[PDB]
Image: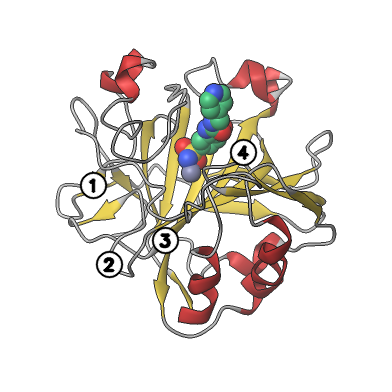
Amino acid sequence: HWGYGKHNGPEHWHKDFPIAKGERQSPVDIDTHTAKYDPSLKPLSVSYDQATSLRILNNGHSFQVTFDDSQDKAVLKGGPLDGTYRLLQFHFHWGSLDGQGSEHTVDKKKYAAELHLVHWNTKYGDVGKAVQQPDGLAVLGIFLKVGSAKPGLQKVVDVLDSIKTEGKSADFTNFDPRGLLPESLDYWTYPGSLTTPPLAECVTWIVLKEPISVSSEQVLKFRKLNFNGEGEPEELMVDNWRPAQPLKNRQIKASFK
Ligand SMILES: NS(=O)(=O)c1ccc(O)c(NC(=O)NCc2ccncc2)c1
Ligand SMILES: [Zn+2]
């Protein structure tokens, strides 16, 4: 029912998900001058060495690669996290044009896309219990800009033709998530929400300072995807991003001076 068009887009979501006007909603603009360097933060430790990708799926608002999370195979720990968070999926948000597409903004600058890597707190047992917890989820957000091609993205790009419309999935084994990470792991962090319905306020956002670059041909193939399912009017999947929400009583902390 909810979507990203004029009639079902982010400005209507509060009618079905009243938490959309809550206190810790996401995304936000990261004012880099008002973020506080916090030395009490630990380095991010990404242990994706034994990650097990399963499928890629068009869910009708994005495409999503899923992982086997029944074991500590790909985990995130450190940073502002307490405990161990298992990788569950990643997905992308992107625009119709290269000057918009990201959900988070940095000094009001929008990037061409955003990669979201979704992890959940193992102490809660499964992901459906974690999403009801104030600290149940950790999302690692990575900006994409348009420049040179990114090799570790090309395997995703090559299969997009197989999942063009909503509900299609394809096998997607032996994918390495480390190929999507920038060279530096400097980050901002703040407590937030999911950026799509149901917009649960369960996320510790970790947003990386350094973007990854992708080529225009690579992003062009993202925009060839469809919101609709097969046998329907053709709606290209673009501008699947929520606009920035007020920070309200929240401080953004930085891991880097
Ligand atoms: N962009 S995000 O903050 O990293 C993010 C991370 C994990 C998520 O699960 C979502 N949200 C969904 O996956 N919503 C599907 C759904 C829609 C309506 N009813 C039930 C389920 C957003
Ligand atoms: Zn997302």
User: Which is more N-terminal, label 1 or label 4?
Assistant: 1
> Which three-letter amino acid code belongs to the residue tagged 1?
Asp
Mark 1 — residue? Answer: 29
Q: CA distance from mark 2 to mark 3?
A: 9 Å
Name the residue: 47% across, 26% down.
1
Which residue is more in the foreground, 101 or 36?
101
Q: Secondary structure at mark 2?
A: loop
Residue at (70% x, 72% y) in the render: 158
Q: In the structure shown, which secondary structural element does the residue marked by tag 3 occupy? A: strand
Bin the neighbour count of mark 4 within 10 Å (Cα to Cα): few under 14, some 14-19, many 20 and up.
many
CA neighbours of label 2 inside 10 A, class few (<14), some (14 to 19), many (20+)? some
Residue 99, labelled with which disc? Answer: 2
Q: Is mark 2 within 8 Å of ligand 2?
A: no
Q: Horizontal and vertical percent for residue 44?
A: 54, 52
Identity of the residue furthest to the left in this view: 33
First reached walking from the N terminus: tag 4 or tag 3: 3
The span from disc 1 to disc 3 (Cα, nearest Å) is 15 Å
Q: Is residue 136 visible?
A: no
Dot 4 or dot 2, earlier in sequence: 2
Q: Where's residue 3, x and y in %?
A: 42, 35
Q: Which residue is mark 3?
A: 113
Please name the amino acid that badge 4 sits on: His
Contact between marks 2 and 3 (CB within 8 A): the answer is no
Callout in the foreground (1, 3): 3
**In the rendered image, which quarter contains the C terminus?**
bottom left
* Amino acid type for the residue under numbered disc 3: Ala
Q: CA distance from mark 4 to mark 2?
A: 28 Å
Point 79% across, 53% down: residue? 170
